[PDB]
């Protein structure tokens, strides 16, 4: 009779609410995983930027160090050359 | 009577189609977010490759510049040495 | 009569199980895509670490090479200077 139909209505309502809430919590799973992976890429981008910046900074420092040493060596070499020249006099 | 049962059938059909289309559009949300995050990682990979390539290129250029300068300095130092030696004669 | 109602029950059960299994397999799609993108970021992180490590290693090697050459050049220059000084005697 209609009683078995009503029991079917209740159990389809139950399973429908079940899949509803399950889907909702699994969407929560997916969205928190999006949040965490986006944070992962954000920190990775920050790491790449920091690495690039400090590598370029050290390249700059080494460049100016080489230039400084070259200048100093030329200058004192000329200085000792003139020193010896005067010592000859 | 069966009329209330029929109204229940219509409203469960309504809510079922509702959750159906909602799930579909939210899956669309998730898949476009996959597409955009994959593009993000793609462009990040391209950025890392470009950074590595230009850093290695500048390292190469600095290496050959140092070698060139060393060679030039040795050569002209020897040249001026021979110049002064001949000037002594 | 109740027969059309029963047919409606069967077809809503069918469509409900259909959306159930479809959602489940599409969640499988989403989770394997999470797995593969997490592996992508993992290998990208490993690549960034390897690049940074070998660049810093080559910077170290170039630094010690420059220091070695500077030391060697100072030393042998002083040596030949003393050599010529003694040759004058």
Image: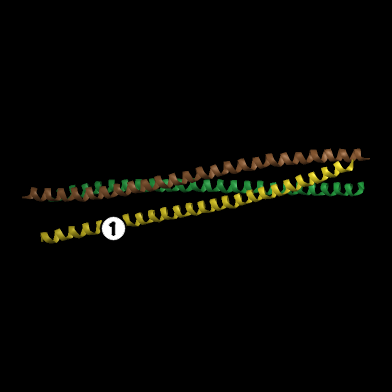
Chain colours: A green, B brown, C yellow
Q: Chain of mark 1?
A: C
At 83% across and 44% down in the image, what residue appears? C7
Expressed as whole percent of the image width and height from the top left, the position of residue B20 reads 73, 41
Q: Is residue C57 above or below residue C4?
A: below
Q: Which residue is mark 1?
A: C71
Q: Is residue B1 above or below residue C39?
A: above
> How many marks do you count on the picture?
1
At 30% across and 48% down in the image, what residue appears? B64
Instruction: Mark yes or no: residue C18 visible.
Output: yes
Expressed as whole percent of the image width and height from the top left, the position of residue C14 reads 77, 46
Expressed as whole percent of the image width and height from the top left, the position of residue B27 reads 66, 42
At 46% across and 55% down in the image, what residue appears? C50
The residue lying toward the viewer, choosing from C30 and B70, is C30
The residue lying toward the viewer, choosing from C88 and B74, is B74
Expressed as whole percent of the image width and height from the top left, the position of residue A41 reads 56, 47
At 73% across and 47% down in the image, what residue appears? C18
Disc 1 on helix, strand or loop? helix
Horizontal side of residue B36 vs C79, given as left or right: right
Horizontal side of residue C25 vs B70, given as left or right: right
- Residue farthest along the left direction in this orientation: B89
Q: Examine the image and state in which quarter residue B7 appears.
A: top right
Q: Examine the image and state in which quarter residue B18 appears.
A: top right
Instruction: Mark yes or no: residue A86 visible.
Output: no
Horizontal side of residue B55 vs B25, given as left or right: left
The residue lying toward the viewer, choosing from B6 and B86, is B6
- Residue farthest along the right direction in this orientation: B1
Q: Residues within 10 Å of mark 1 (few under 14, many from 20)?
A: few
């Amino acid at each position: 009779d209609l009683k078995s139909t009503q029991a079917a209505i209740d159990q389809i309502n139950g399973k429908l609410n079940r899949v509803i809430e399950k889907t909702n919590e699994k969407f929560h799973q997916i969205e928190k995983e999006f949040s965490e992976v986006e944070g992962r890429i954000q920190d990775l981008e920050k790491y790449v930027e920091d690495t690039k910046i400090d590598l370029w900074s050290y390249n700059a420092e080494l460049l100016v160090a080489l230039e400084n040493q070259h200048t100093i060596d030329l200058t004192d070499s000329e200085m000792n050359k003139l020193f010896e020249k005067t010592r000859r006099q």
